[PDB]
Image (spheres, rainbow, N blue to C red):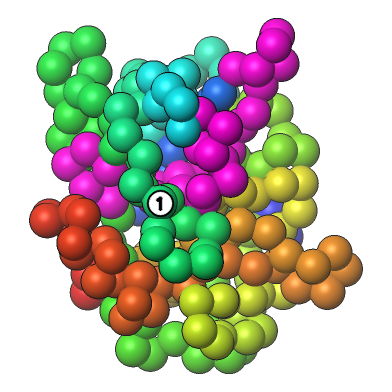
Amino acid sequence: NRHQIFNTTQGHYDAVSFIYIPIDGGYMSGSGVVVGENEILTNKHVVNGAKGNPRNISVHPSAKNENDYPNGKFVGQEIIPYPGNSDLAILRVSPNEHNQHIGQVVKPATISSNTDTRINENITVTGYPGDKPLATMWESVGKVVYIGGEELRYDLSTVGGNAGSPVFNGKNQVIGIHYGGVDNKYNSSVYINDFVQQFLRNNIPDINIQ
């Protein structure tokens, strides 16, 4: 089942972040997770449409609802796509209006080495589902179903559009980034394997992998 998170600044929820991009009086919304001093991990397809101007992307770490942004807003500055064919991107944001960096106002997430990740492992997927009220954070309890290459799949536990949402193991470490799935079969995330970890290390000097 899925449940809303109201204590969005406590513990490992602090780094979970709401991503908002306006489009012609509508918008695109998604999720990501703070992983560095100025860096959000998310999907390529969340930020793709703003490659021409990252400043159109608003990031609200620890957002609670559309009227409650406990850690304010950070504006996109640079997008660093993962070079492989996985739906993964680093979004670098500028400091906020008080000159704070996003990695100072939230504790950046811990990335799992994934040495112990296995089928049937209990996981959570936490972020901003597209079928819920705007900017509300939700946690879904799931089970890993497949691990191969850069793909981690888990059971039909999340719905509504969960692009960019971090997948956490039981130690509250990020093992992957939700991007999609196959309808009525499984959900899919970018698996943070050895290849993905090196990409993070190359771009995020203060990355925390445990």
Q: In which quarter of the image is residue 186?
A: bottom right
Say whether residue 38 is left or right of residue 166.
left
Q: Which of 78 and 186 is in front in this view?
A: 78
Q: In this view, does 208 lie above or below 150?
A: above
Q: In which quarter of the image is residue 202?
A: bottom left
Q: Is residue 58 above or below residue 177?
A: above
Q: Nearer the viewer, residue 118 or 139?
A: 118
Residue 33: give x, y in percent of width and height: 39, 47
Q: Callout 1: 10 Å neighbours few (<14), some, many (20+)?
A: many
Q: Nearer the viewer, residue 140 or 174?
A: 174
Q: Which of 176 and 128 is in front in this view?
A: 176
Residue 146: give x, y in percent of width and height: 63, 86
Indicate yes or no whether the magenta region holds residue 48.
yes
Which residue occupies 40% across, 72% down? Answer: 192
Secondary structure, mark 1, is strand
Specify the segment rendered in magenta: 22-50
> Does any portion of residue 138 appear in the rendered image?
no
Say whether residue 83 is left or right of residue 68.
left
Is the N terminus in the top left, top right, bottom left or bottom right quadrant?
bottom right
Determine the residue located farthest toward the right in the rendered image: 184
Q: Is residue 22 above or below residue 194?
A: above
Which residue occupies 54% across, 39% down? Answer: 48
Is the C terminus in the top left, top right, bottom left or bottom right quadrant?
bottom left
> Does any portion of residue 164 appear in the rendered image?
yes
Residue 87: give x, y in percent of width and height: 54, 58
Please name the residue that numbered disc 1 is placed on. Answer: 81
Indicate yes or no whether the magenta region holds residue 153.
no
Which residue occupies 68% across, 59% down? Answer: 180
Residue 2: give x, y in percent of width and height: 69, 54
Which residue occupies 71% across, 47% down? Answer: 161
The kind of residue tagged 1 is Pro
